[PDB]
Length: 196
Ligand SMILES: *[C@@H]1O[C@H](CO)[C@@H](O[C@@H]2O[C@H](CO)[C@@H](O[C@@H]3O[C@H](CO[C@H]4O[C@H](CO)[C@@H](O)[C@H](O)[C@@H]4O)[C@@H](O)[C@H](O)[C@@H]3O[C@@H]3OC[C@@H](O)[C@H](O)[C@H]3O)[C@H](O)[C@H]2NC(C)=O)[C@H](O)[C@H]1NC(C)=O
Figure (cartoon, rainbow, N blue to C red):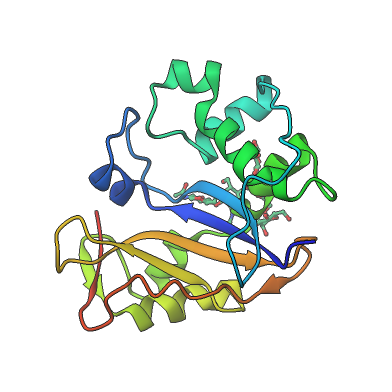
């Protein structure tokens, strides 16, 4: 049994600045993944590999919005579901005792719905278009994560760290909060850009 679940939320504006996007970047956080993990070594590609079934209807519409596959065209994304499949096989495979394909993705949607990080940041006077200290961002998120969240940065331009993703950890059963390991990817010697 793994130690915790990490909900990874992507900030679209940043993701589409550091990567090639085929979808318009939503002005809200989206799901990048839900990773069962351990503090020691990274857990991934657990056996046996779980068969992936293509989603349809409501679940499909829900995932296309909340877990938008930014790197692919909408039609291909909805039809072939490349990113959802990859994430399920690489990470979903590590929590098959408590979840199935449907409840794994359902959980991701439920956990995402628990937060409105954009609004939380705003009430802490942190909005897109400016830069802020790592600590200020961290403190704002912890007000809702309860336990330590993981603020992940990317540097599209050397020397300009920016908010790329936010991780929030939960217990394996997703009933309680858990302290996320700190990736220390943000250069705290300088402010962090919150891309508009
Ligand atoms: C940016 O993204 C965030 C997260 O997705 C958006 O916030 C969420 O927005 C949805 C849609 O407006 C909103 O859904 C509504 O939820 C309430 C109940 O919410 C409470 O209970 C949830 C379960 O216990 C819990 O997860 C929440 O955190 C709240 O405590 C329902 O009563 C409403 O009916 C509505 O639910 C939606 O109904 C339509 C259905 O198709 C859909 O699946 C279902 O979700 C969330 O509450 C809200 N979450 C938060 C934390 O506020 C945010 O709005 C986005 N930004 C903008 C500007 O759009």
